[PDB]
């Protein structure tokens, strides 16, 4: 449950 | 790099790409950001958002 920023 | 996502707040289409407005775990709401869908590894949150809206 993660994400990269920009 | 990658950061823990608490929840998806909203969704939009911009420039032909789906983007999700994210609350980041352990960061204030002022840090919420719109991210293109391919930036997320959040299959559970996305399917829950897309089914409950």
Image (cartoon, helix red, strand yellow):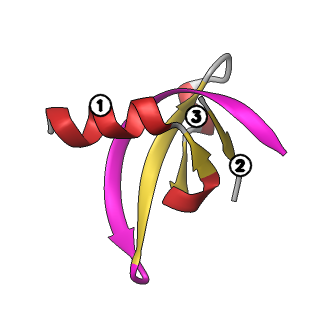
The residue tagged with tag 3: helix, strand or loop? helix
Q: In which quarter of the image is the N terminus of chain B?
A: top right
Q: Which residue bears the numbered disc 2?
A: A4
* Residue beneath the point at 43% across and 83% down: B15
Residue B29 inside the magenta-drawn segment: no
Residue B11 seen in render:
yes
Q: Which residue bears the numbered disc 1?
A: B48
The residue tagged with tag 2: helix, strand or loop? strand
Q: Earlier in the sequence, mark 1 or mark 3?
A: 3
Q: Which residue bears the numbered disc 3?
A: B30
Instruction: Chain letter for mark 3, please.
Output: B
Q: Callout 3: few (<14), some (14-19), or many (20+) C-alpha neighbours within 10 Å?
A: few
| Residue A3 percent location from the top left of the image | 65, 42
Numbered badge on residue B5:
none
The answer to whether B12 is drawn above or below residue A2 in the figure is below
* Residue beneath the point at 42% across and 30% down: B44
Instruction: Chain letter for mark 1, please.
Output: B
Residue B9 inside the magenta-drawn segment: yes
Which span is picked out in magenta? Answer: B1-16
Could you tell whether B36 is left or right of B10 in the image?
Answer: right
Residue B36 seen in render:
no
State the residue in front, B32 or B30: B32
């Amino acid at each position: 449950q993660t994400a990269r920023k920009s | 790099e990658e950061w823990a996502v608490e929840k998806i707040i909203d969704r939009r289409v911009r420039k032909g790409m789906v983007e999700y407005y994210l609350k980041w775990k352990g960061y204030p709401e002022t840090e919420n950001t719109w991210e293109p869908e391919n930036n997320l590894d959040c299959q559970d949150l996305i399917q829950q958002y897309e089914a409950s809206r």
